[PDB]
Length: 122
Length: 122
Ligand SMILES: Cn1cc(C#CCn2cnc3c(c(-c4cccc(C#N)c4)cn3CC(=O)Nc3ccncc3Cl)c2=O)cn1
Ligand SMILES: Cn1cc(C#CCn2cnc3c(c(-c4cccc(C#N)c4)cn3CC(=O)Nc3ccncc3Cl)c2=O)cn1
Ligand SMILES: [Cl-]
Ligand SMILES: [Cl-]
Ligand SMILES: [Cl-]
Ligand SMILES: [Cl-]
Image 1 (tube, each protein chain N blue to C red):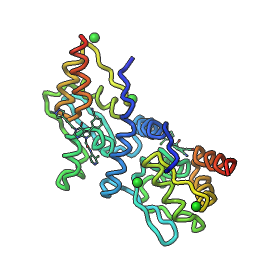
Image 2: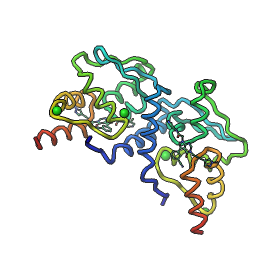
Image 3: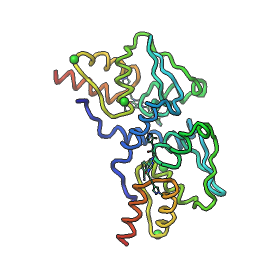
Image 4: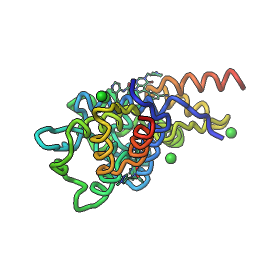
């Protein structure tokens, strides 16, 4: 019965991305080979089965640094981190395989499914 | 040029509300007279000019407890906190004035404007 605000969730996500761009209340750095990316653990948990499983565990919840598998492509990771904070996925012929493999590792099914649709559409 | 995921922002907000319901990575309690409400500072900053102004200030960013004005109605506050995390506003004849005054204090213009529309619609 409540009044629905159709733009509200997008407004929240935009403001969370603005906080990330200023490093405000970021609480983790994700290390991907020679690169590092700061983020909010809450957003990572909201968007990734891997990060959900890491930070729900009381053993790991307070970690300030997460080292990803050294095989993960930093560009693929950055594309997916930007997707988490924007709802926009930068998929191209030159990055689809790295993005798809990274989304499998991060446990991000809708992106993996979208990568399969991209391949089927050539 | 990116692929747009129209449901993604709502999915993120739902998962942030699920984390709030489990008290996972909440980092502040908001005290409203005899009641207390836990939340994520990032979501509060994303949805309120008052909380943005409090937590952007390096003087106050690390506060774990915020005491609101003792005049603020706890039910009005709870309605607006739920709106922040759901995009749904529970506006009724019995709560409109308290919700509107609380939204003015929290600096939440779209809700204040919606309260004005509710009054104009009787
Ligand atoms: C090999 N492989 C495994 C998979 C997988 C997969 C499945 N999968 C699993 N977990 C996921 C997601 C998502 C999610 C969210 C938004 C966009 C996208 C995308 N794109 C994904 C969040 N999460 C964590 C969660 O559900 N968080 C949560 C749950 C309950 N309460 C609070 C919180 Cl935070 C997901 O897709 C793919 N390949
Ligand atoms: C007396 N009175 C003053 C006012 C006012 C008012 C105006 N107002 C001011 N600030 C606001 C909002 C919002 C906001 C967001 C979503 C829904 C609603 C509603 N409903 C409001 C966020 N915010 C903080 C911000 O803009 N955060 C942010 C900005 C830039 N980067 C990162 C971040 Cl987190 C707002 O409405 C009304 N009455
Ligand atoms: Cl971005
Ligand atoms: Cl390309
Ligand atoms: Cl709720
Ligand atoms: Cl009523």
